[PDB]
Length: 217
Length: 6
Length: 218
Image (cartoon, rainbow over all chains, first blue to last red; front, side, top):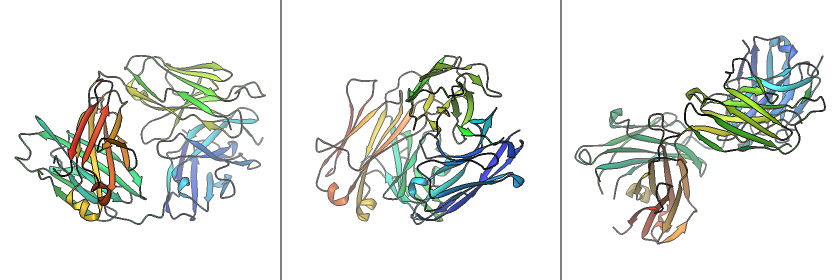
């Protein structure tokens, strides 16, 4: 079966560079044009660049030309994207994609890889501020606000994981250059504040865990 | 929309 | 460039029902070779797009019979005749008649369920954040359906939009509801200029807004 596997993503400073590769198998690579397609969070895909099967034609989207260079080496079954002068608006999942053809036209991108992620940011790795959310009804809703961290991986755990089905984890959002998310939990009024309820916030990149006890105001 | 290399 | 316009942006459907998604190009998609290079893709969470239909109506290898495409000129339709849980995801149309190839904005296929009014909870800033010099007012709106909901923040009875960040969970896999977090972030100084803080939600489940409030000096 057709397989495409890209690599070379990572986090770079604005103005930094990247060279992505895409390894191809399960088809005669030199018979097919190939493309790069990128996709930011929440957005549709956006075509980036194209190279014909013997590399006589190369085209570039307006948003990248000058800065990116697409290339291929048919004997290594590998496609390349060198990227320079990177800006935060270049942050995206980058996909390698095969173009199919029946005659003289490359007309549809039919097989796509799983993508390699490129983040362009000047943010330093920063541990989050963890803020308790307590009410200052049969059921009671609590929360923790997890504010101003980078990069994205955090995990919120309530009561060592025993509370889980009543939890909402809200997706992080960028602002002031950093991420912010929140988590809510809903327990019966019989259980809180009668019993204890704690959010544990792990930020692996900054090697921080903060346990915050929810105290009635 | 691109030209193939025959 | 050719602008691909998809409607709806979001499409609730009952499993076993038929879904229909439309795509409109800003120019004719008939190539000089006579083909119409209009394609549909399906993207599932955490995966790349997969081609479903190419050249208006050809099913790609392994695409089941229930996917059907039609249309001509500038107006195109994809039909899923009996939606199954594996078909949930984001569909895109794409054109390859003109350079550059372009994509629609997407249509999220989502699950239908009975209406459910949100549970709304408002939370003042913590003393710890005020010590840090900021003041976030948080409001949770949990377990509602449909996904459409409008949240307004009122400070002392007056609306505010600067400093509000809204976050939506995906459709819950067990009750098919949605949840949302609305966070109003002020400096400590702005927080201390005002006393009444209100989270206000309008959802189709009532003509009356759900109002949640606290007073800072209480």
